[PDB]
Amino acid sequence: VKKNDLFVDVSSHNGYDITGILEQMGTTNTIIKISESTTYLNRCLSAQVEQSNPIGFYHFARFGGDVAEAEREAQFFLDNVPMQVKYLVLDYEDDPSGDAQANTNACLRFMQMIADAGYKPIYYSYKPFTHDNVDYQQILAQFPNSLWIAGYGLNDGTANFEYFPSMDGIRWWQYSSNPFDKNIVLLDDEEDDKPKTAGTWKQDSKGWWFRRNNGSFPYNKWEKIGGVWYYFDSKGYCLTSEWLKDNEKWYYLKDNGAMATGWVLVGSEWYYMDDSGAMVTGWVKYKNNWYYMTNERGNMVSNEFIKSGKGWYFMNTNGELADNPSFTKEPDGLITVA
Ligand SMILES: C[N+](C)(C)CCO
Ligand SMILES: C[N+](C)(C)CCO
């Protein structure tokens, strides 16, 4: 998954049919509960798996500060993973021991066994509980950006950045549980490795061109080199800092020719692109600030409104906010948090 992607988490509480809540949410990405302690298995597992696209599974911990118990739970969890997924989550929110360092150690041993089994470990919890019962920093030192924290606020079923949990290493944010558990992604999944490419980059007075292994080179086309996309001139030079209309959709190629994804500052205007590079028009919120973007007839416009208190103030590109707010009631657009 990519930044701002959504996913739902479920357990027996959601029953053998979750097609409805996946439709309401608008995604099939799910993290399903497999086990609890060393004896409980979520009965709806296979059904919930079948009805969605799992990105991970979670275990409800009951080991407290006992490392030997955490090991037995991790193993029971592992022995029941039904299919390969990138993540296996440690849901630590109950029965903490009075000894925070012991809680941390058991949590670390649990996460370590998940990592040794070939998965990316995730620590799930709530800020206050984590603050009182463990040293999440000691966890991040061994497992960077491995946190999945919950923080609902009003819990009205929507993502409200005003109540966004402040902690380092937060990978996922469960922003609500109102109807069902809703989560939004803050960091792209990792992909360390994939070294070398299928050619060599060449630079010169005219810019950069790519010499493929066989001597040829891309031109008048898009092409994925490394993990990123680029568009090449009819001469084989990749575009830089430029807009490109391709197939009725707009794309922006950054300073390094790399196709933009997510938020990107062009000049002094903000624009938001699909995970596939296509510009997204209309209302889109970046954290606390709202942007109404449009590209009709190729006229790129970014209407910025900075939040201040209980209001949003329009900011004319002349660098000045109005004296009074433009709106105190947020529009119903795409919410992004990173
Ligand atoms: C060489 N570029 C700057 C064009 C990008 C890939 O390294
Ligand atoms: C389709 N593009 C080549 C424009 C990029 C997304 O894969």
Image (tube, grey):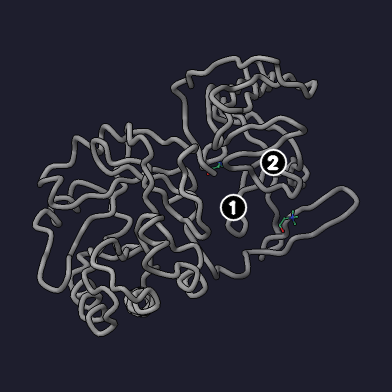
Q: Nearer the viewer, residue 134 or 315?
A: 134
Q: Residue at x 15, y 56 (%)?
A: 45
Label 1 CB sits under 8 Å from any ligand 2 atom = yes
What's the CA distance linking mark 2 and mark 1?
A: 13 Å
The image shows residue 247 at horizontal and vertical percentages of 56, 29
Q: Amino acid at mark 1?
A: Lys
Which quarter shows the C terminus?
A: top right
Label 2 CB sits under 8 Å from any ligand 1 atom = no
Q: Residue at x 91, y 51 (%)?
A: 205
Q: Residue at x 59, y 22 (%)?
A: 312
Residue for badge 1: 224
Q: Is residue 97 above or below residue 254?
A: below
Q: Residue at x 33, y 40 (%)?
A: 176
Does 302 sit left or right of 85 as displayed?
A: right
Element on which disc 1 rests: strand
Q: Amino acid at mark 2?
A: Leu
The quarter of the displayed image where residue 103 is located:
bottom left
Does 19 sit left or right of 133 as displayed?
A: left
Q: Is residue 270 above or below residue 312?
A: below
Q: Is residue 16 above or below residue 190?
A: above
Residue for badge 2: 253
Q: Quadrant of ligand 1?
A: bottom right
Disc 2 or 1, which lies upstream in sequence? 1
Is residue 124 among the parts visible in the rendering? Answer: yes
Q: Nearer the viewer, residue 245 or 330?
A: 330
* Mark nearer the viewer, 2 or 1: 2
Q: Is residue 282 above or below residue 278?
A: above
The image shows residue 333 at horizontal and vertical percentages of 46, 25
Is residue 117 among the parts visible in the rendering? Answer: no
Does 195 sit left or right of 130 as displayed?
A: right
